[PDB]
Amino acid sequence: TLPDMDTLRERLLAGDRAALARAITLAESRRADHRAAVRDLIDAVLPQTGRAIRVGITGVPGVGKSTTIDALGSLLTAAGHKVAVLAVDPSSTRTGGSILGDKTRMARLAIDRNAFIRPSPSSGTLGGVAAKTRETMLLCEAAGFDVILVETVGVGQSETAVADLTDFFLVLMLPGAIKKGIFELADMIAVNKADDGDGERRASAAASEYRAALHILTPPSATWTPPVVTISGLHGKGLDSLWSRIEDHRSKLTATGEIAGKRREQDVKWMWALVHERLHQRLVGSAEVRQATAEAERAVAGGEHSPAAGADAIATLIGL
Amino acid sequence: PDMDTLRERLLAGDRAALARAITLAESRRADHRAAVRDLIDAVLPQTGRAIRVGITGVPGVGKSTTIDALGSLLTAAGHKVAVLAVDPSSTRTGGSILGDKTRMARLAIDRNAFIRPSPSSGTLGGVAAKTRETMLLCEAAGFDVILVETVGVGQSETAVADLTDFFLVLMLPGAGDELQGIKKGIFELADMIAVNKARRASAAASEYRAALHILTPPSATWTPPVVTISGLHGKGLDSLWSRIEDHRSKLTATGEIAGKRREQDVKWMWALVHERLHQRLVGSAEVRQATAEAERAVAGGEHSPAAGADAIATLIGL
Image (cartoon, rainbow over all chains, first blue to last red; front, side, top):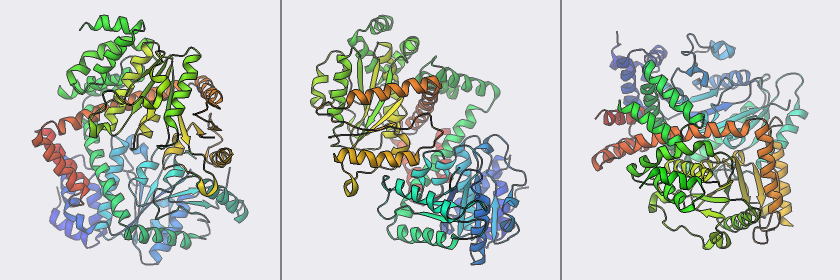
Protein backbone atom coordinates (compact mmCIF):
# COMPACT_ATOMS: atom_id res chain seq x y z
CA THR A 1 0.00 0.00 0.00
CA LEU A 2 2.92 2.41 0.58
CA PRO A 3 4.54 2.96 -2.87
CA ASP A 4 8.20 2.13 -3.47
CA MET A 5 9.55 5.36 -2.01
CA ASP A 6 12.91 5.27 -3.80
CA THR A 7 11.06 4.96 -7.11
CA LEU A 8 8.65 7.74 -6.13
CA ARG A 9 11.54 10.03 -5.12
CA GLU A 10 13.49 9.47 -8.34
CA ARG A 11 10.39 10.08 -10.48
CA LEU A 12 9.45 13.21 -8.54
CA LEU A 13 13.01 14.56 -9.03
CA ALA A 14 12.65 13.96 -12.79
CA GLY A 15 9.58 16.25 -12.88
CA ASP A 16 7.02 13.42 -12.89
CA ARG A 17 3.74 15.28 -12.18
CA ALA A 18 1.93 12.13 -10.99
CA ALA A 19 4.77 11.39 -8.56
CA LEU A 20 4.54 14.94 -7.17
CA ALA A 21 0.75 14.58 -6.80
CA ARG A 22 1.20 11.23 -5.02
CA ALA A 23 3.77 12.60 -2.61
CA ILE A 24 1.34 15.45 -1.74
CA THR A 25 -1.45 12.86 -1.21
CA LEU A 26 0.76 10.80 1.11
CA ALA A 27 1.22 13.89 3.32
CA GLU A 28 -2.57 13.97 3.97
CA SER A 29 -2.84 10.25 4.71
CA ARG A 30 -4.71 8.99 7.76
CA ARG A 31 -1.73 6.67 8.24
CA ALA A 32 1.20 7.95 10.30
CA ASP A 33 3.65 5.77 8.31
CA HIS A 34 2.58 7.37 5.03
CA ARG A 35 3.10 10.86 6.42
CA ALA A 36 6.51 9.78 7.82
CA ALA A 37 7.57 8.38 4.45
CA VAL A 38 7.00 11.68 2.69
CA ARG A 39 8.82 13.59 5.47
CA ASP A 40 11.81 11.30 4.76
CA LEU A 41 11.37 12.02 1.03
CA ILE A 42 11.36 15.78 1.57
CA ASP A 43 14.52 15.73 3.70
CA ALA A 44 16.12 13.43 1.08
CA VAL A 45 15.38 15.91 -1.74
CA LEU A 46 16.24 19.08 0.20
CA PRO A 47 19.38 19.87 -1.88
CA GLN A 48 17.18 20.06 -4.99
CA THR A 49 14.86 22.66 -3.42
CA GLY A 50 15.09 26.42 -3.13
CA ARG A 51 15.81 27.22 -6.80
CA ALA A 52 12.51 29.04 -7.26
CA ILE A 53 11.09 32.48 -6.77
CA ARG A 54 8.58 32.27 -3.91
CA VAL A 55 5.90 34.96 -4.05
CA GLY A 56 3.06 35.41 -1.59
CA ILE A 57 -0.07 37.14 -2.92
CA THR A 58 -2.97 38.60 -0.97
CA GLY A 59 -5.91 40.97 -1.46
CA VAL A 60 -9.53 41.37 -0.28
CA PRO A 61 -12.10 39.24 -2.20
CA GLY A 62 -13.28 41.00 -5.38
CA VAL A 63 -9.91 42.62 -6.05
CA GLY A 64 -9.51 40.13 -8.92
CA LYS A 65 -6.92 37.88 -7.32
CA SER A 66 -7.80 34.70 -9.31
CA THR A 67 -7.99 36.63 -12.55
CA THR A 68 -4.64 38.34 -11.94
CA ILE A 69 -2.88 35.11 -10.89
CA ASP A 70 -4.32 33.30 -13.93
CA ALA A 71 -3.00 36.06 -16.18
CA LEU A 72 0.43 36.37 -14.58
CA GLY A 73 0.84 32.59 -14.25
CA SER A 74 -0.02 32.17 -17.93
CA LEU A 75 2.51 34.81 -18.99
CA LEU A 76 5.08 32.95 -16.93
CA THR A 77 4.34 29.46 -18.34
CA ALA A 78 4.34 30.91 -21.89
CA ALA A 79 7.88 32.18 -21.07
CA GLY A 80 8.92 28.61 -20.17
CA HIS A 81 8.50 28.77 -16.39
CA LYS A 82 6.89 26.01 -14.34
CA VAL A 83 4.44 27.64 -11.94
CA ALA A 84 2.93 26.23 -8.76
CA VAL A 85 -0.07 27.95 -7.15
CA LEU A 86 -0.71 26.97 -3.53
CA ALA A 87 -3.62 28.28 -1.46
CA VAL A 88 -3.53 28.98 2.30
CA ASP A 89 -6.92 29.35 4.02
CA PRO A 90 -7.35 29.21 7.81
CA SER A 91 -10.74 27.53 7.21
CA SER A 92 -8.99 24.27 6.15
CA THR A 93 -8.63 23.79 9.94
CA ARG A 94 -12.44 23.37 9.91
CA THR A 95 -13.27 21.46 6.68
CA GLY A 96 -11.08 18.37 6.24
CA GLY A 97 -9.53 20.13 3.22
CA SER A 98 -10.68 20.17 -0.41
CA ILE A 99 -11.53 16.86 -2.04
CA LEU A 100 -10.91 18.06 -5.63
CA GLY A 101 -9.54 21.57 -5.10
CA ASP A 102 -10.79 24.64 -6.93
CA LYS A 103 -8.33 25.07 -9.82
CA THR A 104 -11.02 26.17 -12.30
CA ARG A 105 -11.09 29.62 -10.64
CA MET A 106 -7.98 30.12 -12.80
CA ALA A 107 -9.39 28.97 -16.12
CA ARG A 108 -6.19 29.03 -18.20
CA LEU A 109 -3.84 27.66 -15.55
CA ALA A 110 -6.34 24.92 -14.66
CA ILE A 111 -5.69 23.08 -17.96
CA ASP A 112 -1.98 24.03 -18.25
CA ARG A 113 0.41 21.17 -17.42
CA ASN A 114 3.16 23.75 -16.98
CA ALA A 115 1.23 24.80 -13.84
CA PHE A 116 0.33 22.91 -10.67
CA ILE A 117 -2.53 24.14 -8.46
CA ARG A 118 -3.31 22.87 -4.94
CA PRO A 119 -5.85 23.90 -2.28
CA SER A 120 -5.14 24.74 1.38
CA PRO A 121 -4.15 21.60 3.32
CA SER A 122 -6.06 20.32 6.37
CA SER A 123 -4.44 20.68 9.83
CA GLY A 124 -5.37 21.42 13.44
CA THR A 125 -3.80 24.90 13.66
CA LEU A 126 -2.96 27.70 11.20
CA GLY A 127 0.73 27.05 12.00
CA GLY A 128 0.07 23.43 10.97
CA VAL A 129 -1.59 24.44 7.68
CA ALA A 130 1.30 26.80 6.90
CA ALA A 131 3.95 24.20 7.88
CA LYS A 132 2.29 21.68 5.54
CA THR A 133 2.22 24.29 2.77
CA ARG A 134 6.00 24.71 3.26
CA GLU A 135 6.35 20.91 2.76
CA THR A 136 4.31 21.13 -0.41
CA MET A 137 6.43 24.04 -1.66
CA LEU A 138 9.59 21.97 -1.16
CA LEU A 139 8.08 19.03 -3.08
CA CYS A 140 7.10 21.32 -5.98
CA GLU A 141 10.59 22.85 -6.09
CA ALA A 142 12.29 19.41 -6.08
CA ALA A 143 10.00 18.44 -8.98
CA GLY A 144 11.30 21.41 -11.02
CA PHE A 145 8.79 24.17 -10.38
CA ASP A 146 10.72 27.46 -10.50
CA VAL A 147 7.95 29.88 -9.54
CA ILE A 148 5.90 29.20 -6.41
CA LEU A 149 2.88 31.47 -5.90
CA VAL A 150 1.26 31.20 -2.49
CA GLU A 151 -2.16 32.85 -2.25
CA THR A 152 -4.25 33.79 0.78
CA VAL A 153 -7.76 32.41 0.27
CA GLY A 154 -10.85 33.01 2.42
CA VAL A 155 -11.57 35.81 4.91
CA GLY A 156 -9.43 34.72 7.93
CA GLN A 157 -5.99 35.77 9.21
CA SER A 158 -3.48 34.11 6.86
CA GLU A 159 -1.47 37.08 5.60
CA THR A 160 1.41 36.90 8.07
CA ALA A 161 1.70 33.12 7.53
CA VAL A 162 1.93 33.58 3.73
CA ALA A 163 4.51 36.40 4.12
CA ASP A 164 6.49 33.98 6.33
CA LEU A 165 6.24 31.22 3.65
CA THR A 166 7.64 33.32 0.76
CA ASP A 167 10.46 35.66 -0.37
CA PHE A 168 8.28 38.49 -1.66
CA PHE A 169 4.85 39.59 -0.50
CA LEU A 170 2.52 41.22 -3.05
CA VAL A 171 -0.64 43.01 -1.93
CA LEU A 172 -3.41 43.62 -4.49
CA MET A 173 -5.64 46.62 -3.73
CA LEU A 174 -8.78 48.07 -5.35
CA PRO A 175 -8.89 51.69 -6.62
CA GLY A 176 -11.41 52.32 -3.85
CA ALA A 177 -14.82 51.29 -2.53
CA ILE A 178 -8.00 46.35 4.32
CA LYS A 179 -6.72 44.81 7.60
CA LYS A 180 -4.27 47.44 8.77
CA GLY A 181 -1.20 45.15 9.24
CA ILE A 182 -1.09 44.30 5.53
CA PHE A 183 0.74 47.50 4.48
CA GLU A 184 3.78 46.60 6.60
CA LEU A 185 3.93 43.10 5.13
CA ALA A 186 4.00 44.46 1.58
CA ASP A 187 7.10 44.31 -0.62
CA MET A 188 4.90 45.86 -3.33
CA ILE A 189 1.35 47.09 -3.67
CA ALA A 190 -0.48 46.70 -7.00
CA VAL A 191 -3.72 48.62 -7.50
CA ASN A 192 -5.78 46.41 -9.83
CA LYS A 193 -8.42 47.56 -12.31
CA ALA A 194 -11.35 45.14 -11.67
CA ASP A 195 -13.79 46.00 -14.43
CA ASP A 196 -14.90 48.71 -16.90
CA GLY A 197 -15.51 51.08 -13.98
CA ASP A 198 -11.76 51.15 -13.19
CA GLY A 199 -9.33 52.98 -15.43
CA GLU A 200 -5.99 54.69 -15.04
CA ARG A 201 -7.50 57.74 -13.29
CA ARG A 202 -9.02 55.77 -10.39
CA ALA A 203 -6.06 53.32 -10.25
CA SER A 204 -3.32 55.96 -10.35
CA ALA A 205 -5.22 58.13 -7.81
CA ALA A 206 -5.29 55.26 -5.29
CA ALA A 207 -1.65 54.33 -6.08
CA SER A 208 -0.51 57.89 -5.34
CA GLU A 209 -2.24 57.85 -1.95
CA TYR A 210 -0.63 54.52 -1.02
CA ARG A 211 2.75 55.69 -2.33
CA ALA A 212 2.57 58.86 -0.22
CA ALA A 213 1.57 56.97 2.94
CA LEU A 214 4.28 54.29 2.51
CA HIS A 215 6.83 57.12 2.74
CA ILE A 216 6.30 57.34 6.56
CA LEU A 217 7.03 53.62 6.98
CA THR A 218 10.66 52.58 7.15
CA PRO A 219 11.45 49.74 4.70
CA PRO A 220 12.86 46.75 6.66
CA SER A 221 15.81 46.41 4.22
CA ALA A 222 17.90 49.26 2.84
CA THR A 223 18.16 47.02 -0.27
CA TRP A 224 14.47 47.36 -1.22
CA THR A 225 11.92 50.17 -1.07
CA PRO A 226 8.37 48.80 -1.73
CA PRO A 227 6.88 50.19 -4.96
CA VAL A 228 3.24 50.95 -5.71
CA VAL A 229 2.07 50.12 -9.22
CA THR A 230 -1.11 49.80 -11.27
CA ILE A 231 -2.21 46.74 -13.25
CA SER A 232 -5.18 45.13 -14.94
CA GLY A 233 -5.43 41.38 -14.30
CA LEU A 234 -8.49 41.23 -16.56
CA HIS A 235 -6.65 42.73 -19.58
CA GLY A 236 -3.14 41.47 -18.73
CA LYS A 237 -1.67 44.97 -18.50
CA GLY A 238 1.31 45.98 -16.31
CA LEU A 239 2.05 42.35 -15.37
CA ASP A 240 5.40 42.06 -17.19
CA SER A 241 6.52 45.21 -15.41
CA LEU A 242 5.20 43.86 -12.08
CA TRP A 243 7.18 40.64 -12.57
CA SER A 244 10.36 42.50 -13.50
CA ARG A 245 10.20 44.27 -10.12
CA ILE A 246 9.93 40.90 -8.30
CA GLU A 247 12.92 39.60 -10.30
CA ASP A 248 14.87 42.77 -9.41
CA HIS A 249 14.10 42.16 -5.71
CA ARG A 250 15.31 38.57 -6.09
CA SER A 251 18.55 39.63 -7.82
CA LYS A 252 19.34 42.37 -5.33
CA LEU A 253 18.51 40.47 -2.14
CA THR A 254 20.26 37.32 -3.32
CA ALA A 255 23.49 39.34 -3.83
CA THR A 256 23.25 40.60 -0.20
CA GLY A 257 22.40 37.15 1.19
CA GLU A 258 19.08 38.53 2.46
CA ILE A 259 16.86 36.00 0.59
CA ALA A 260 18.76 33.10 2.26
CA GLY A 261 18.76 34.92 5.64
CA LYS A 262 14.99 35.34 5.60
CA ARG A 263 14.45 31.73 4.45
CA ARG A 264 16.52 30.31 7.33
CA GLU A 265 14.47 32.30 9.88
CA GLN A 266 11.29 31.02 8.25
CA ASP A 267 12.57 27.45 8.28
CA VAL A 268 13.11 27.51 12.07
CA LYS A 269 9.63 29.04 12.48
CA TRP A 270 8.01 26.23 10.49
CA MET A 271 10.00 23.63 12.48
CA TRP A 272 8.50 24.92 15.73
CA ALA A 273 5.07 25.31 14.10
CA LEU A 274 5.01 21.54 13.49
CA VAL A 275 6.21 20.88 17.09
CA HIS A 276 3.31 23.07 18.30
CA GLU A 277 0.72 21.45 15.99
CA ARG A 278 1.73 18.06 17.35
CA LEU A 279 1.29 19.38 20.91
CA HIS A 280 -2.16 20.66 19.92
CA GLN A 281 -3.03 17.26 18.47
CA ARG A 282 -2.14 15.68 21.80
CA LEU A 283 -4.34 18.19 23.66
CA VAL A 284 -7.35 17.25 21.48
CA GLY A 285 -6.50 13.56 20.97
CA SER A 286 -9.52 12.36 22.92
CA ALA A 287 -12.93 13.88 23.83
CA GLU A 288 -11.94 14.07 27.50
CA VAL A 289 -8.66 15.87 26.86
CA ARG A 290 -10.23 18.25 24.32
CA GLN A 291 -12.96 19.07 26.84
CA ALA A 292 -10.41 19.81 29.57
CA THR A 293 -8.19 21.91 27.28
CA ALA A 294 -11.21 23.92 26.09
CA GLU A 295 -12.29 24.55 29.68
CA ALA A 296 -8.81 25.77 30.78
CA GLU A 297 -8.87 28.17 27.83
CA ARG A 298 -12.44 29.27 28.65
CA ALA A 299 -11.58 29.88 32.33
CA VAL A 300 -8.67 32.09 31.20
CA ALA A 301 -10.73 33.91 28.56
CA GLY A 302 -13.35 34.55 31.23
CA GLY A 303 -10.94 36.02 33.81
CA GLU A 304 -11.69 33.20 36.24
CA HIS A 305 -8.11 31.89 36.40
CA SER A 306 -5.02 33.74 35.23
CA PRO A 307 -3.11 32.80 32.05
CA ALA A 308 -0.38 31.09 34.17
CA ALA A 309 -2.98 29.05 36.07
CA GLY A 310 -4.50 27.95 32.74
CA ALA A 311 -1.10 26.98 31.42
CA ASP A 312 -0.41 24.94 34.58
CA ALA A 313 -3.79 23.17 34.11
CA ILE A 314 -2.76 22.28 30.53
CA ALA A 315 0.60 21.04 31.89
CA THR A 316 -1.20 18.57 34.17
CA LEU A 317 -3.09 17.17 31.18
CA ILE A 318 0.16 16.55 29.30
CA GLY A 319 1.60 14.81 32.39
CA LEU A 320 -1.52 12.61 32.63
CA PRO B 1 4.94 32.45 54.60
CA ASP B 2 1.13 32.61 54.91
CA MET B 3 -0.46 33.21 51.50
CA ASP B 4 -3.88 34.04 52.95
CA THR B 5 -2.34 36.82 55.06
CA LEU B 6 -0.35 37.95 52.02
CA ARG B 7 -3.53 38.14 49.91
CA GLU B 8 -5.55 40.08 52.50
CA ARG B 9 -2.75 42.62 52.96
CA LEU B 10 -2.21 43.05 49.20
CA LEU B 11 -5.94 43.66 48.69
CA ALA B 12 -5.95 46.32 51.43
CA GLY B 13 -3.29 48.22 49.50
CA ASP B 14 -0.20 47.02 51.45
CA ARG B 15 2.57 47.87 48.95
CA ALA B 16 5.16 45.56 50.58
CA ALA B 17 2.73 42.65 50.40
CA LEU B 18 2.20 43.49 46.70
CA ALA B 19 5.97 43.47 46.10
CA ARG B 20 6.33 40.11 47.88
CA ALA B 21 3.57 38.57 45.69
CA ILE B 22 5.16 40.01 42.53
CA THR B 23 8.55 38.54 43.50
CA LEU B 24 6.91 35.08 43.68
CA ALA B 25 4.98 35.51 40.40
CA GLU B 26 8.06 36.71 38.53
CA SER B 27 10.42 34.12 40.13
CA ARG B 28 12.65 31.96 37.97
CA ARG B 29 12.01 29.24 40.57
CA ALA B 30 9.06 27.06 39.60
CA ASP B 31 8.16 26.35 43.26
CA HIS B 32 7.92 30.07 44.02
CA ARG B 33 5.68 30.73 41.00
CA ALA B 34 3.51 27.71 41.95
CA ALA B 35 3.11 29.07 45.50
CA VAL B 36 1.32 32.28 44.38
CA ARG B 37 -1.04 30.81 41.70
CA ASP B 38 -4.10 30.45 43.98
CA LEU B 39 -3.49 33.93 45.43
CA ILE B 40 -3.59 35.46 41.93
CA ASP B 41 -6.75 33.53 40.98
CA ALA B 42 -8.42 34.47 44.28
CA VAL B 43 -7.86 38.16 43.57
CA LEU B 44 -9.06 38.16 39.92
CA PRO B 45 -12.51 39.60 40.73
CA GLN B 46 -10.69 42.77 41.91
CA THR B 47 -8.74 43.21 38.66
CA GLY B 48 -9.49 44.96 35.35
CA ARG B 49 -10.54 48.36 36.75
CA ALA B 50 -7.42 50.08 35.44
CA ILE B 51 -6.35 51.79 32.22
CA ARG B 52 -3.50 49.70 30.78
CA VAL B 53 -1.16 51.69 28.50
CA GLY B 54 1.87 50.42 26.59
CA ILE B 55 4.53 52.97 25.74
CA THR B 56 7.43 52.64 23.31
CA GLY B 57 9.97 54.84 21.53
CA VAL B 58 13.55 54.76 20.30
CA PRO B 59 16.40 55.32 22.80
CA GLY B 60 16.80 59.11 23.07
CA VAL B 61 13.17 60.02 22.28
CA GLY B 62 12.49 61.13 25.88
CA LYS B 63 10.47 58.08 26.96
CA SER B 64 11.66 58.05 30.60
CA THR B 65 11.22 61.82 30.96
CA THR B 66 7.72 61.61 29.45
CA ILE B 67 6.65 58.70 31.66
CA ASP B 68 8.01 60.55 34.71
CA ALA B 69 6.02 63.68 33.86
CA LEU B 70 2.82 61.87 32.86
CA GLY B 71 2.95 59.61 35.96
CA SER B 72 3.39 62.71 38.17
CA LEU B 73 0.41 64.45 36.59
CA LEU B 74 -1.61 61.31 37.20
CA THR B 75 -0.62 60.88 40.86
CA ALA B 76 -1.24 64.59 41.48
CA ALA B 77 -4.78 63.93 40.18
CA GLY B 78 -5.30 61.12 42.73
CA HIS B 79 -4.41 58.15 40.52
CA LYS B 80 -2.42 55.17 41.76
CA VAL B 81 0.16 54.45 39.03
CA ALA B 82 2.18 51.29 38.38
CA VAL B 83 5.07 51.45 35.91
CA LEU B 84 6.24 48.06 34.62
CA ALA B 85 9.01 47.32 32.11
CA VAL B 86 9.54 44.59 29.53
CA ASP B 87 13.24 44.22 28.62
CA PRO B 88 14.44 41.50 26.15
CA SER B 89 18.03 41.90 27.51
CA SER B 90 16.93 40.22 30.76
CA THR B 91 17.62 36.91 28.95
CA ARG B 92 21.32 37.84 28.78
CA THR B 93 21.66 39.46 32.20
CA GLY B 94 19.32 37.47 34.48
CA GLY B 95 17.40 40.76 34.88
CA SER B 96 18.03 43.69 37.20
CA ILE B 97 17.45 43.67 40.97
CA LEU B 98 17.13 47.44 41.38
CA GLY B 99 16.35 48.51 37.80
CA ASP B 100 17.12 52.12 36.91
CA LYS B 101 15.15 55.03 38.39
CA THR B 102 17.73 57.77 37.78
CA ARG B 103 15.54 58.08 34.70
CA MET B 104 12.26 58.78 36.50
CA ALA B 105 13.56 60.83 39.43
CA ARG B 106 10.29 62.39 40.69
CA LEU B 107 8.19 59.26 40.28
CA ALA B 108 10.85 57.10 41.92
CA ILE B 109 10.23 58.77 45.28
CA ASP B 110 6.47 59.27 44.85
CA ARG B 111 4.71 56.71 47.13
CA ASN B 112 1.55 57.00 44.97
CA ALA B 113 3.55 55.29 42.23
CA PHE B 114 5.00 51.78 42.07
CA ILE B 115 7.84 51.15 39.65
CA ARG B 116 9.19 47.68 38.85
CA PRO B 117 12.11 46.58 36.71
CA SER B 118 11.55 44.04 33.94
CA PRO B 119 11.32 40.39 35.15
CA SER B 120 13.72 37.81 33.80
CA SER B 121 13.01 34.67 31.94
CA GLY B 122 14.96 32.61 29.45
CA THR B 123 12.86 34.31 26.73
CA LEU B 124 10.93 37.50 25.90
CA GLY B 125 7.58 35.60 25.89
CA GLY B 126 8.24 34.43 29.47
CA VAL B 127 9.14 37.98 30.50
CA ALA B 128 5.91 39.40 29.06
CA ALA B 129 3.68 36.65 30.51
CA LYS B 130 5.11 37.28 33.98
CA THR B 131 4.38 40.98 33.45
CA ARG B 132 0.70 40.04 32.83
CA GLU B 133 0.49 38.25 36.22
CA THR B 134 2.19 41.23 37.85
CA MET B 135 -0.29 43.64 36.23
CA LEU B 136 -3.20 41.63 37.69
CA LEU B 137 -1.62 41.75 41.16
CA CYS B 138 -1.17 45.52 40.84
CA GLU B 139 -4.80 46.00 39.79
CA ALA B 140 -6.02 43.81 42.70
CA ALA B 141 -3.94 46.05 45.01
CA GLY B 142 -5.87 49.12 43.74
CA PHE B 143 -3.66 50.60 41.03
CA ASP B 144 -5.94 52.24 38.47
CA VAL B 145 -3.27 53.11 35.90
CA ILE B 146 -0.78 50.53 34.61
CA LEU B 147 1.98 51.87 32.34
CA VAL B 148 4.08 49.20 30.58
CA GLU B 149 7.31 50.40 28.92
CA THR B 150 9.46 48.75 26.27
CA VAL B 151 13.01 48.94 27.63
CA GLY B 152 16.43 48.57 25.95
CA VAL B 153 17.23 47.28 22.47
CA GLY B 154 15.17 44.38 21.16
CA GLN B 155 11.76 43.96 19.62
CA SER B 156 9.42 43.97 22.60
CA GLU B 157 6.75 46.18 20.99
CA THR B 158 4.33 43.42 20.04
CA ALA B 159 4.66 41.91 23.53
CA VAL B 160 3.87 45.25 25.20
CA ALA B 161 0.97 45.93 22.80
CA ASP B 162 -0.40 42.50 23.74
CA LEU B 163 -0.12 43.38 27.46
CA THR B 164 -2.14 46.59 27.28
CA ASP B 165 -5.37 48.30 26.14
CA PHE B 166 -3.74 51.23 24.34
CA PHE B 167 -0.34 51.41 22.63
CA LEU B 168 1.40 54.78 22.58
CA VAL B 169 4.30 55.45 20.26
CA LEU B 170 6.68 58.34 21.12
CA MET B 171 8.50 59.77 18.10
CA LEU B 172 11.32 62.20 17.31
CA PRO B 173 10.43 65.70 15.99
CA GLY B 174 12.34 65.54 12.64
CA ALA B 175 10.35 66.27 9.46
CA GLY B 176 10.87 65.98 5.67
CA ASP B 177 14.40 64.68 5.09
CA GLU B 178 14.67 64.32 8.87
CA LEU B 179 11.43 62.36 9.34
CA GLN B 180 12.10 59.45 11.72
CA GLY B 181 9.77 56.96 10.01
CA ILE B 182 7.79 54.11 11.58
CA LYS B 183 9.69 50.80 11.95
CA LYS B 184 8.12 47.68 10.42
CA GLY B 185 5.22 46.35 12.47
CA ILE B 186 4.81 49.44 14.66
CA PHE B 187 2.12 51.26 12.59
CA GLU B 188 -0.32 48.40 12.99
CA LEU B 189 0.26 48.52 16.79
CA ALA B 190 -0.07 52.28 17.29
CA ASP B 191 -3.18 53.73 18.92
CA MET B 192 -1.57 57.18 19.09
CA ILE B 193 1.65 58.82 17.99
CA ALA B 194 3.08 61.56 20.20
CA VAL B 195 5.85 63.63 18.69
CA ASN B 196 8.12 64.66 21.57
CA LYS B 197 10.69 67.41 22.33
CA ALA B 198 8.50 70.20 20.91
CA ARG B 199 7.56 73.72 14.95
CA ARG B 200 9.37 70.83 13.25
CA ALA B 201 7.43 68.64 15.72
CA SER B 202 4.10 69.95 14.38
CA ALA B 203 5.46 69.43 10.85
CA ALA B 204 6.36 65.80 11.63
CA ALA B 205 2.96 65.27 13.29
CA SER B 206 1.20 66.52 10.13
CA GLU B 207 3.16 64.01 7.99
CA TYR B 208 2.39 61.08 10.28
CA ARG B 209 -1.29 62.12 10.59
CA ALA B 210 -1.85 62.37 6.81
CA ALA B 211 -0.33 58.93 6.23
CA LEU B 212 -2.15 57.34 9.18
CA HIS B 213 -5.41 58.60 7.71
CA ILE B 214 -4.64 56.94 4.34
CA LEU B 215 -3.61 53.66 6.03
CA THR B 216 -6.41 53.36 8.60
CA PRO B 217 -9.63 51.70 7.27
CA PRO B 218 -12.72 53.91 7.64
CA SER B 219 -14.43 50.94 9.41
CA ALA B 220 -12.14 51.25 12.50
CA THR B 221 -13.74 52.33 15.79
CA TRP B 222 -10.54 54.23 16.55
CA THR B 223 -8.36 56.36 14.26
CA PRO B 224 -5.01 57.03 16.01
CA PRO B 225 -4.55 60.70 17.02
CA VAL B 226 -1.19 62.31 16.29
CA VAL B 227 -0.23 64.91 18.90
CA THR B 228 2.82 66.92 19.92
CA ILE B 229 4.13 67.01 23.49
CA SER B 230 7.13 68.04 25.53
CA GLY B 231 7.90 65.45 28.20
CA LEU B 232 10.55 67.68 29.79
CA HIS B 233 8.26 70.72 30.14
CA GLY B 234 5.04 68.72 30.62
CA LYS B 235 3.24 70.34 27.69
CA GLY B 236 0.41 68.48 25.96
CA LEU B 237 0.34 65.61 28.47
CA ASP B 238 -3.12 66.37 29.82
CA SER B 239 -4.47 66.32 26.24
CA LEU B 240 -2.55 63.12 25.49
CA TRP B 241 -4.05 61.39 28.54
CA SER B 242 -7.55 62.60 27.67
CA ARG B 243 -7.34 60.78 24.29
CA ILE B 244 -6.46 57.56 26.12
CA GLU B 245 -9.61 58.05 28.21
CA ASP B 246 -11.52 58.73 24.99
CA HIS B 247 -10.34 55.37 23.59
CA ARG B 248 -11.40 53.58 26.79
CA SER B 249 -14.83 55.20 26.59
CA LYS B 250 -15.39 54.46 22.90
CA LEU B 251 -14.07 50.89 22.90
CA THR B 252 -15.83 49.93 26.14
CA ALA B 253 -19.13 50.90 24.48
CA THR B 254 -18.42 48.49 21.60
CA GLY B 255 -17.17 45.78 24.00
CA GLU B 256 -13.76 45.97 22.25
CA ILE B 257 -11.71 46.67 25.43
CA ALA B 258 -13.05 43.47 27.04
CA GLY B 259 -12.74 41.49 23.81
CA LYS B 260 -9.09 42.43 23.37
CA ARG B 261 -8.22 41.50 27.00
CA ARG B 262 -9.82 38.08 26.51
CA GLU B 263 -7.78 37.41 23.36
CA GLN B 264 -4.59 38.63 25.07
CA ASP B 265 -5.07 36.42 28.13
CA VAL B 266 -5.58 33.30 26.01
CA LYS B 267 -2.51 34.30 23.95
CA TRP B 268 -0.43 34.55 27.17
CA MET B 269 -1.75 31.16 28.30
CA TRP B 270 -0.55 29.45 25.10
CA ALA B 271 2.73 31.43 25.24
CA LEU B 272 3.33 29.90 28.70
CA VAL B 273 2.41 26.37 27.52
CA HIS B 274 4.92 26.70 24.66
CA GLU B 275 7.55 28.20 26.98
CA ARG B 276 7.15 25.23 29.38
CA LEU B 277 7.68 22.81 26.45
CA HIS B 278 10.83 24.61 25.45
CA GLN B 279 12.05 24.62 29.08
CA ARG B 280 11.71 20.83 29.15
CA LEU B 281 13.66 20.67 25.87
CA VAL B 282 16.52 22.60 27.51
CA GLY B 283 16.13 21.09 31.04
CA SER B 284 19.58 19.48 31.17
CA ALA B 285 22.87 19.92 29.30
CA GLU B 286 22.41 16.72 27.29
CA VAL B 287 18.84 17.58 26.24
CA ARG B 288 19.74 21.18 25.41
CA GLN B 289 22.60 19.90 23.24
CA ALA B 290 20.19 17.70 21.23
CA THR B 291 17.59 20.44 20.86
CA ALA B 292 20.34 22.83 19.69
CA GLU B 293 21.51 20.21 17.16
CA ALA B 294 17.99 19.96 15.73
CA GLU B 295 17.56 23.73 15.45
CA ARG B 296 21.07 24.25 14.03
CA ALA B 297 20.37 21.60 11.34
CA VAL B 298 17.30 23.54 10.19
CA ALA B 299 18.85 27.04 10.63
CA GLY B 300 21.86 25.87 8.61
CA GLY B 301 19.78 24.46 5.74
CA GLU B 302 21.15 20.95 6.39
CA HIS B 303 17.80 19.28 7.09
CA SER B 304 14.18 20.19 6.43
CA PRO B 305 12.05 21.97 9.10
CA ALA B 306 9.99 18.77 9.65
CA ALA B 307 13.20 16.73 10.10
CA GLY B 308 14.14 19.17 12.90
CA ALA B 309 10.65 18.75 14.34
CA ASP B 310 10.97 14.94 14.14
CA ALA B 311 14.25 15.13 16.11
CA ILE B 312 12.43 17.19 18.78
CA ALA B 313 9.60 14.60 18.83
CA THR B 314 12.19 11.88 19.58
CA LEU B 315 13.49 13.97 22.49
CA ILE B 316 9.99 14.56 23.84
CA GLY B 317 9.43 10.78 23.75
CA LEU B 318 12.63 10.23 25.75
